[PDB]
Image (cartoon, rainbow over all chains, first blue to last red):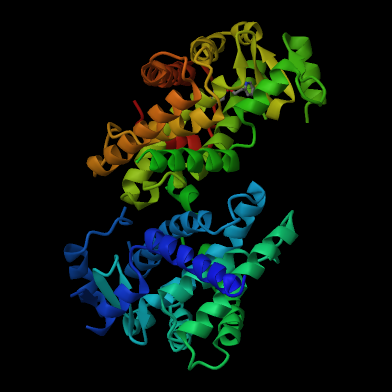
Amino acid sequence: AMGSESADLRALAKHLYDSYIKSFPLTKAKARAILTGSPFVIYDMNSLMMGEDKIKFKHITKEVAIRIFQGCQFRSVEAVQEITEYAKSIPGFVNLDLNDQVTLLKYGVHEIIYTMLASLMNKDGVLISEGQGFMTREFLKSLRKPFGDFMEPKFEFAVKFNALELDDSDLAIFIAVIILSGDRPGLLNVKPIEDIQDNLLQALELQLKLNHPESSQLFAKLLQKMTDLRQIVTEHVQLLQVIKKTETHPLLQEIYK
Amino acid sequence: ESADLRALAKHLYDSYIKSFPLTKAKARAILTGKTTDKSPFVIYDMNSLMMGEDKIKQSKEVAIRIFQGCQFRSVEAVQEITEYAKSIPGFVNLDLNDQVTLLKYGVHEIIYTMLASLMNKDGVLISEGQGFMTREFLKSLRKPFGDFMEPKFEFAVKFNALELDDSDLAIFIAVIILSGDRPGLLNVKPIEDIQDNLLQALELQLKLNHPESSQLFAKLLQKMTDLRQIVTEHVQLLQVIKKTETDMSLHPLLQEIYKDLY
Ligand SMILES: CCc1ccc(CCOc2ccc(C[C@@H]3SC(=O)NC3=O)cc2)nc1
């Protein structure tokens, strides 16, 4: 029995890494290799126009700021399905009450999207179209109000988050901790979700201790980032309030809400 | 790959349960009175219709009010079906125009597939299982509405004879959505490749769940011919209705679906 707890936690961590690799083809490791230095760079309106020829976008059915926002929504819809697939491989998740599964995902996917978005970001821009393109932070910032300000807070979060230097094996456990959050509103069976999250937290803590021995209290630091993810999501939900009440297919509208 | 196809089948069943509150299993339980709950209210004539509208809980003429009730149920189903479609692996990665086309052309085929789950040869469950409207009452409605539901009943009787359950239907409805022959599709092969995988998953599901049912896979695919004819004939009936009725306020969602459809 000596060492068996450790071994079980490392086995869970490896299981989550392996499934994360299957659910998310464009890993942080691959993204960082692209970002450090080939993708087509969109750095202004003109290069965005030629970018449309070099890259086949799937969301084009208008004004440039609106098309970019719709492109981001298309990608987020794809990410919801990748995250839902990944969640099925979190031990315990599929055996939960079906309604609680839906609830956990409804509230979890946005926090996860912005966590994983940081893997594709550096301080100067973001990979798009599976690494085929790179859009500068400055170009996004330049878009007309209120679209100039919709990606900037995500960049702010990502620069700080990426300074933790987490890798894919760390993130796989962290995103599972996020999904198994017992405090989402409307959950029927809270105790089993907390039990699963307890074991995931143990696994995350041991993973960070072994992978980042030089990083004092990285576990605590990473848990604290949950306050900023929740801030980012809340703030982002408010901005989606504006866009639907100041800006402007019926099936298309259905696909997304 | 066997385990991949079983994992696909289980994923679709789960998302089907998440997306469709009134399953065939529940519809069947109500139809045969097997669990708790009080029997549904039976509407078999004009007097029982009048009272059913009082107990079960805005045109004035009866045939139009029933037709509009069917339209409202359809809008609801479209919302459930589109929610389901997003869960089909690969669907949301398609060109967005093709996503819209697949839903435009698939949604009624699925509506009539799942309508069969609420039908027997004598009538159809309505209002979330709180009512049961008889087939003979529906056939009594004035022209051209006495012919509205009858072809759907003819389909349901033949389709229900296949004895599918919800786990079978979840894969079947995904096969319907991922049809590469819809008019106006831009990227056909990505859709066909997905449907190919769904067809492999459906074939294995039928062989495991229905080992004694010879050629059930083929017989189920043959019902796709019958579903297409129900939809195209329903569009025909809509053209007759346009000529026989005064204003028909059609829900805008149905307006877009029907726009330039057959
Ligand atoms: C209380 C009136 C009533 C309530 C629901 C049903 C059962 C539903 O049968 C249906 C029949 C047709 C549809 C398709 C509807 S009707 C139409 O023109 N377009 C549609 O999408 C959808 C459901 N029967 C009678």
